[PDB]
């Protein structure tokens, strides 16, 4: 009969055809069913995966465990949960790539319209150039410099640390004081040792330096004064010409100098070897100056200006008979000279009668004396006898 | 006749075939036209999308708005603009993935040969490990420590800030000076308050400390001296043995000590009671030294070396009739002793005639006296009379 | 016999069919060979690339070099090296996207089960939000602030640098000392100049300030004392009432003041004019006190407390014949007053006979005198004579 396929009219074929030679088409192939090719496949321009109610995907099979094959199969799936009526409906459009175990990564647009690219592990780029914000929850390490156009802010008590060689140096704000601190040697990332180089009180701003301070090029305290425990060495500049040296703006002020070299101290006043004499009548001793002897001593200056300046010279003894004598002088700005050193009068260096214009108590000579009431010589009193217009004698 | 398909030779079919049963092929299928499968599709090893003049793509349809379907369709497109003759021809090879609204991401090889991976939103990895450079234009926040092998550099005036509790501490380089500054309490991320703990002049390096300074373990000024407004309390170390204590390298220098305890000051010189006498002839007063009375006082030392050192002792009055007296001594290194304190002579503590070997102004006694010109007793003048080897007595009215 | 195809029975076609009209299928198409479509292709729900020994891939052809075509073809390949491929066996499953030259990016799960997403160039997101760690090997730049909840640590000698205007300020830990340093003007990223504002010794914590120090609001040295090279100007607060001013807790201590204005110095003691006289008998000179002359001077105070406090007043000459005199007084807390200034006795300002109750050396008057041994008038000794109960004269 005509149970054969017509070659020129539209035919429905109810046999299962097996084409053993190349099949050539020049018109659309339209199937309601599946396709399977045991060889490779190619199409022009576009491949569309149609969706009739279940999300579309591509599957990349792992194949046998040999050659260049993967350990697991992979897929690309385009899906969402906006329409699923679940507890999460915010994953509107998701492009997900992953294997049998879990996703590797996905991009998604959420219901709010914003895009996220999630990586289920470590992102390893060469460079990073982000136009927006960065947040990193874990520890960060940088191999070179880090430059910000803004401020670096730490919320950690130990905030900024510089490590080099054996030591970490760090700034610590402990909420009460901010400290500059140091580690033990070889403990560069660890805690502070016992040193307290510098701290600032967070409330008052007062600074404490705890391990000593050296300053070069001068100090000025503008206000509030100075308290020192427990000595001050103000060390004057010792020059060969101290005896005659005019003060300058650099050398005014308080200082002391140990003048211990004879080339200098021979120019200054000496001490006097003292000679003890004894009053013939009372037996009380008194001192008189013997020879002047040059001596080392301390030169101390006081006063703050080229007008207001004076010095003290205190000899110090370096031999058994040596004694200390003090001398003073004043800078005379208008005369452009030091006053001459004058000796301080003290119990070790008293003034003599001849220094003051007083009669010696012993062996004295004078031009004239007037006695009002009586002169006694040994046991005779000589008194005025105005009646006989003379003097009366009077044994006692 | 030949309006039927042959099973044995090549055959052109000119009617539309509908195959209702499975079709098997064992040789290539070559179409110059489209393919449409209402079911799923599979191929072996490689799928190739061919390009005859327009970029190639895969389209993932969104389907009905139900189940696990996406809200928008997506595509993968491979394209470029190197050959399009536009103002931009630098996007040489682009792999772009996105939806109906915009791309989600793309990778691109630029015309310069370098690769970029652009993400149109937020990237959310677990770890990051970059072998090259990082740039971030916006604010950065880190949850733990940040370690660099290089330098941290800020171009912001407020450059480095440590926040803890109520306060921010920060370093500010304002182009003229660099300051160490503090915020008001509870204003930790804000501006500086009025405090000026420390600043450094950027030109000279000179430091100003603005809120006071405490120092432990010594200060040395190497050069330039010291100016102080407006007093210096150099507080010496007070010990029970100050009267006899040899100086040490630690105690040389200038200081003062208030010796206010009698166990110590009773070892030191006292002040002297003074009696005011009157010269009978002239009526002018003079002070006669009385009893020494022990007293608290100030001990002040000067000198900087174990050779060059001396002290002043200035008593101060604590009772209604007490006076003040000053005393001095000097350290004697070669004797290993202080000289004995000696009294300073001054208008309140004058030298006494017996101290100096001067005759008292009245009621006096002496061994002998020589008069050259005259001695007068009452109205009698006694004068030399050498021609008679005697003296004359002249009443002189 | 029947070299024609049955339209209702399973057939094996052995010549090449060329179909010129639309082919419809309603059952599976199953091929052991390849497919090639010159138009677009579509399938429902899933596309699977089967793997029978070689890794699966999709190839996107580059086409002619015109329009919107890419310069190179691209592929997505899913492969691994766990089962072959040289010396590395750790790349278990790799999803690789790239062109003819190299990969652009890949995701992979390694043998240990961990996922990496590798980008062969620059990643350019808007925001970054990493839940784990960050490492960046190259230089890093931030456009705004950088906040860390932890510590910032630098291993670079030059550790923290703040740049503004012409200068960089930086903290440098050089292993031995930590320095606060400054650049030359206009060399903001460069080395330190010669300035040494501040350094901390890493071992002792001792601080050195190298370019001068100003302090406001007071200084206290708690221990260790003070050494100064080479002067100290302790400048007291000059007020109009210095003569009578009671000390306060703020004004106790050591200082000097130049009292240069007569309104104030006229209240203080002057110097005394002196005339040099000569003792006629001995030829020895002595200074005789004359008028007080008001003078500017230096007031210096010593002592640290409201009990322990005293002052020196040292006049200085401002006219050609002016002398210098020193005066002293002590603060008397219990009397709430300064003692009266008293004159210092020195070689330029000796005591006078009237100060001490001594007889002047000549031209003198007194009430009475007792002579134990002899009175000599001219060359006659007047001595006591017991035998007549008067005096005898003896020529010498």
Image (cartoon, coloured by chain):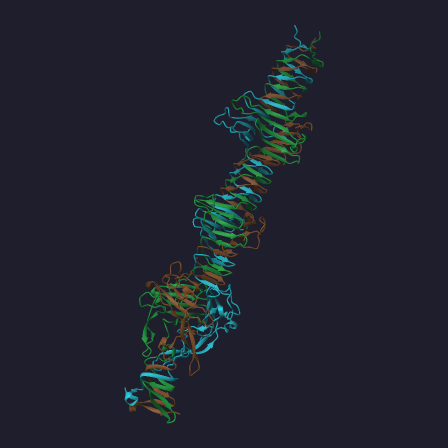
Chain colours: A green, B brown, C cyan
- Closer to the camera, B296 or A76? B296
- In the picture, which quadrant includes the C terminus of chain A? bottom left
- Can residue C381 be seen in the rendering of this structure? no
Residue B114, percent from left and from top: 55, 34
- In the picture, which quadrant includes the N terminus of chain A? top right
Residue A324, percent from left and from top: 36, 68
Q: Is B116 situated above or below A375?
A: above
Q: Image check: B27 left or right of C294?
A: right
Q: Is C102 situated above or below C315?
A: above
Q: Image check: C186 left or right of A311?
A: right
- Can residue A287 be seen in the rendering of this structure? yes
Q: Residue furthest bottom?
A: A388
The residue drawn where x is 53% and y is 41% is B144
The residue drawn where x is 41% and y is 64% is B263
Residue A127, percent from left and from top: 54, 37
Residue C383 image-quadrant placement:
bottom left
């Amino acid at each position: 009969p005509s149970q054969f396929i017509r070659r020129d009219i539209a035919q429905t074929v109810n046999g299962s055809l097996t084409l053993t030679q190349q099949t050539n088409l020049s018109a659309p192939l339209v199937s309601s069913s599946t396709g399977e090719f045991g060889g490779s496949l190619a199409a022009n321009r576009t491949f569309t995966i149609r969706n009739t109610g279940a999300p579309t995907s591509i599957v990349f099979e792992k194949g046998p465990a040999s050659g260049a094959n993967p350990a697991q199969s992979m897929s690309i799936r385009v899906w969402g949960n906006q329409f699923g009526g679940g507890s999460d409906t915010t994953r509107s459009t998701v492009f997900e790539v992953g294997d049998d175990t879990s996703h590797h990564f996905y991009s998604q647009r959420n219901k709010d319209g914003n895009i996220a690219f999630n990586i289920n592990g470590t992102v390893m780029p060469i460079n990073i150039n982000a136009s927006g914000l960065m947040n990193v929850n874990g520890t960060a390490t940088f191999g070179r410099s880090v430059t910000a156009n803004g401020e670096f802010i730490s919320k950690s008590a130990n905030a900024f640390r510089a490590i080099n060689g054996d030591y970490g140096f760090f700034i610590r704000n402990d909420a009460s004081n901010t400290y500059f601190l140091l580690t033990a040697a070889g403990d560069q990332t660890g805690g502070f040792n016992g040193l307290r180089p510098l701290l600032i009180n967070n409330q008052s701003g007062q600074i404490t330096i705890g391990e000593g301070l050296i300053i070069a090029k001068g100090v000025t305290i503008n206000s509030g004064g100075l308290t020192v425990n427990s000595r001050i060495r103000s060390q004057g500049t010792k020059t060969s010409d101290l005896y005659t040296r005019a003060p300058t703006s650099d050398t005014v002020g308080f200082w002391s100098i140990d003048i211990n070299d004879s080339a200098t101290y021979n120019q200054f006043p000496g001490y006097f070897k003292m000679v003890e004499k004894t009053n013939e009548v009372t037996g009380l001793p008194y001192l008189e100056r013997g020879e002047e002897v040059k001596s080392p001593g301390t030169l101390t200056q006081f006063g703050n200006t080229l007008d207001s300046l004076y010095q003290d010279w205190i000899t110090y003894p370096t031999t058994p008979e040596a004694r200390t004598t003090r001398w003073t002088r004043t800078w005379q700005k208008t005369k452009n000279s030091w006053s001459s050193f004058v000796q301080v009068f003290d119990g070790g260096n008293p003034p003599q009668p001849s220094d003051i214009g007083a009669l010696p108590s012993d062996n004295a000579t004078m031009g004239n004396l007037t006695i009002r009431d009586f002169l006694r010589i040994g046991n005779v009193r000589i008194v005025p006898d105005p009646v006989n217009k003379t003097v009366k004698f009077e044994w006692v």
